Amino acid sequence: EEHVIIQAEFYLNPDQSGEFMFDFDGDEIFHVDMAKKETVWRLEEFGRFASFEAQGALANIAVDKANLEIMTKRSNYTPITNVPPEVTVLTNSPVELREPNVLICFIDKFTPPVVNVTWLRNGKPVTTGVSETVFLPREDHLFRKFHYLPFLPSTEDVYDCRVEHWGLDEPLLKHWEFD
Amino acid sequence: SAVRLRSSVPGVR
Amino acid sequence: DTRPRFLEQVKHECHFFNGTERVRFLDRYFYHQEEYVRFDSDVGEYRAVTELGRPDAEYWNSQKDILEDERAAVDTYCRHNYGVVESFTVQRRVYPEVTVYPAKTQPLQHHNLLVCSVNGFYPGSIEVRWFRNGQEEKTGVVSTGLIQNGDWTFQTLVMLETVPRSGEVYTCQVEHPSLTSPLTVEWRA
Ligand SMILES: *[C@@H]1O[C@H](CO)[C@@H](O[C@@H]2O[C@H](CO)[C@@H](O)[C@H](O)[C@H]2NC(C)=O)[C@H](O)[C@H]1NC(C)=O
Ligand SMILES: *[C@@H]1O[C@H](CO)[C@@H](O)[C@H](O)[C@H]1NC(C)=O
Ligand SMILES: *[C@@H]1O[C@H](CO)[C@@H](O)[C@H](O)[C@H]1NC(C)=O
């Protein structure tokens, strides 16, 4: 098997969250920002080569919501079982003092697709420059997610990715520091 | 060119 | 928040073999993680995966228009979309940046570990091997495995457990589809 393309959707109650994305071999091609009704390409350049009418995603998500209602009843209101995430913190490239790098917080193998993620520098929340992906599908039908923090490596700062999820009894902190 | 979506189908009530 | 959650997922999958020469469409519906009904182009009708999906299989199979939309999808959906995105996905090639540096199994010791850091490559299939004085070292090799960065690049670290001696030349060798010949990086004690 050479390649797989997947148009993956979900809808979650009672949160009323829906997602729509396309995956190629485990990487996101794009997703639809449901609130803005706009196609968001994972890499900038993708959108120069291709287009997607975001409106069609909204239509599908509406069907998914109706179907969730139906299936919820069929199941006799059997709820999802929380599966807490595995969390790993790593850098984009080998770290050198005062050379711009990126911390990656990889949050894997969890469901439902709801998390609170915070970057901490010296124990304090940081938000400047941060970015994140949507919930990405796994072949076992759990989810994964990436959060990113550009930083200037120094011996002065330590970092943590703090992840909250209903499957965890307390927030999970994964640490990173120089050396 | 345009990516085409696969419709999701309404189930039975 | 302890309110119960309920999740519906749909995955419309296109599977490609030898480009668009052989293509399989798998339309999948899930309640939580449980796949309950699917259309497989190999079959050409919906089948219930669990009892939960029996009503949908039976109804959707009664709707000739739905069935024919599903049957055409290998062409109008899978083959079409492959055409649209293949130039920046299928054909994507990013060569790795390779670095070699010493490390410690314990922060207090001397160096007893060599790291070959392979960063920023696409696609994921890669072969990384260690050589000492031109002979491949296959013992004491350990790795992160293949790591997705989530941004259409991968990385991997491949370690050689060794105590370097003067005179020795170590080489990390990398083979990858973006490369027309092996990329090698030398390190000397
Ligand atoms: C993420 O954090 C928020 C805030 O604590 C939690 O969501 C709820 O926030 C709203 C107000 O913004 C309120 O409805 C609730 O008071 C919060 N939940 C609780 C604790 O009752 C949310 O639960 C957190 N998400 C996860 C997955 O931990
Ligand atoms: C829900 O309850 C009905 C009535 O007892 C039963 O027929 C059906 O099997 C149940 N569905 C389940 C257990 O998912
Ligand atoms: C792949 O396709 C080529 C031309 O499209 C064909 O000649 C070849 O038989 C295929 N490869 C296989 C089945 O090994």
Image: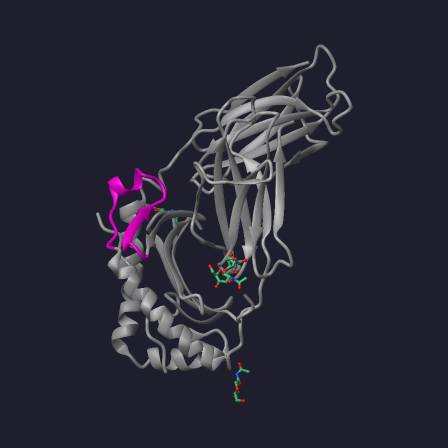
**Looking at the image, residue A46 lies above or below residue C108:** below
Query: Could you tell me which quadrant the C terminus of chain A lies in?
Result: top right
Coordinates of residue A100 in the picture (x, y in percent): 48, 26
Coordinates of residue A54 in the picture (x, y in percent): 26, 55
**Looking at the image, residue A121 lies above or below residue A143:** above
Q: Give residue A64's quadrant in the image.
A: bottom left
Q: Is residue A51 left or right of residue A82?
A: left
The answer to whether residue C97 of the structure is visible from this angle is: yes
How many numbered circles does the render carry? 0
Which color mode does the image show?
one colour
Camera-nearest residue between C150 and A2: C150
For this orientation, the residue located farthest to the top is C167
Magenta run includes residue A42 = yes
Question: Residue at (36%, 81%) from the top-left corner?
Answer: B12
Camera-nearest residue between C120 and C179: C120
The answer to whether residue C12 of the structure is visible from this angle is: no
Camera-nearest residue between C54 and C23: C54
Magenta run includes residue C114 = no
Point out the stretch of residues depicted in magenta: A34-53
For this orientation, the residue located farthest to the front is A124
Q: Give residue C53's quadrant in the image.
A: bottom left
Query: What is the chief secondary structure element of the magenta stretch?
Result: loop
Question: Residue at (27%, 42%) from the top-left corner?
Answer: A47
Question: Residue at (59%, 44%) from the top-left corner?
Answer: A88
Coordinates of residue C59 in the picture (x, y in percent): 35, 81
For this orientation, the residue located farthest to the left is B1
Q: Is residue C63 left or right of residue A134?
A: left
**Looking at the image, residue A146 lies above or below residue C111:** below
Coordinates of residue C119 in the picture (x, y in percent): 51, 30
